[PDB]
Image (cartoon, rainbow over all chains, first blue to last red; front, side, top):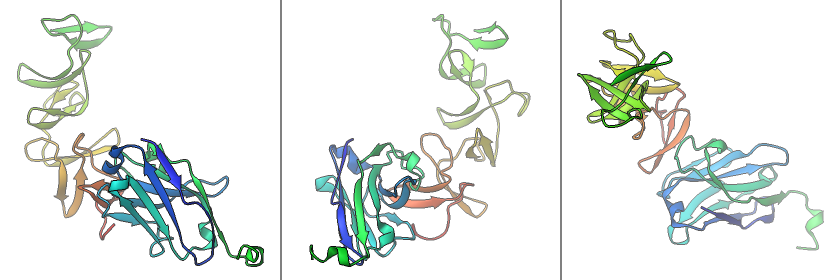
Length: 132
Length: 136
């Protein structure tokens, strides 16, 4: 069970970004899948998890209403759609599989991990003018 | 049959030279063996999960002998079980004393200590195994 993440980069505060977590095998679809995020030197904190069925979800109170986790069975891919992004959401994001379906908030319960990708939310303004 | 090595009793099948393994009925007693040694714990027999108990837990049982154990919880090596009227550990969704629990299908141990996916849905269980209110 190999996991490949994509979609990382930089967005302005209030903006949106969608991350992808694509699996190499059909077995992925049988298990719940979570996103965790980690600041430098810090621990991997829970963000969201989705059931194998794709219809049951749990969010960190911090992101409920702003973030949506979903999956596409045909593409063997789980997504994190991030809206109304805040500087507080700046972190390295990981997706992970919990094949035992046990204690979904705890990263130590997860047995396969994506490689992690940087998401940066900028709330400063003047350093972005040339790109804009 | 039964032999003593060093100090502990082991059981061997009449067709082998290495100790018995798994569920066994011996002279109206139930055991669950590992390389001849009776195991203490909650294991699956032909009519569900039984409590193979430490010696002198009930009716002077020996170590690993299955016992009567009715209508009560058991804490065993930190795992939570509940035994019904028939002395078998319950499985699946159960309401006990007004509280809901989910006992896992492979072990009969209570789901405990956070979020679990069960029947395709996410639920929350307290550290005590009790299902928390609301939608997760």
